[PDB]
Image 1 (cartoon, chains in turn orange, green):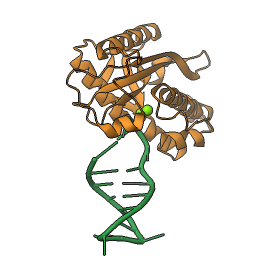
Image 2 (cartoon, chains in turn cyan, brown):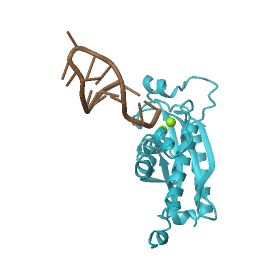
Image 3 (tube, rainbow, N blue to C red):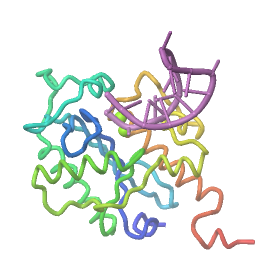
Image 4 (spheres, chains in turn brown, green):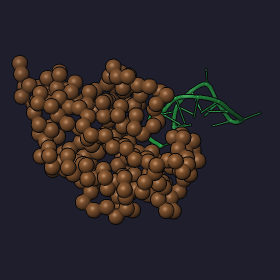
Length: 208
DNA sequence: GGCCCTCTTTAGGGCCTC
Ligand SMILES: [Mg+2]
Ligand SMILES: [Mg+2]
């Protein structure tokens, strides 16, 4: 009934990033939010700790106008409250390592919607920032797009949430914190629903 | 931004991770 037993020792952390393009190697990371998860005594999954950072474009970063048009971020607004990629990820890594330790897990796995996108940008930023002992799995992810495909027959984040009976506000979409929060609730609902229907634990699946 | 589909090509709009 513990978090460490649910995903073979992986500590699931929900991540959403905002960027200045689709190229993780060359395009700026502009924003990141992280949500750790916890399991109660009954084995139900729910959000734990929330982190959120506005990120300064790394020196020499490429910025695509169409991306900025999409996410509405102005990297030149001085009142952004932006910090370096190093600062943002160092704090996220610290909180995640603390969570891994306390929960008895072995390492973290990124939960994200179309997770390869966020995973690729996180790894790139961590490499640029020279961060060491990255607690995230270097290639495995929990993609909520695929999970929603299974659980709900939908792959688009907004539609998956709506289909799951969740609230989803289009006026708040495409903002990092809101997207991460909805993705975390969606992941938790998918996992909890599997348990409600008797698919987990495996002993329950074997009944009748 | 650009590939893809089609009620296509002398084009528009869906895609839905930025
Ligand atoms: Mg996203
Ligand atoms: Mg987003």
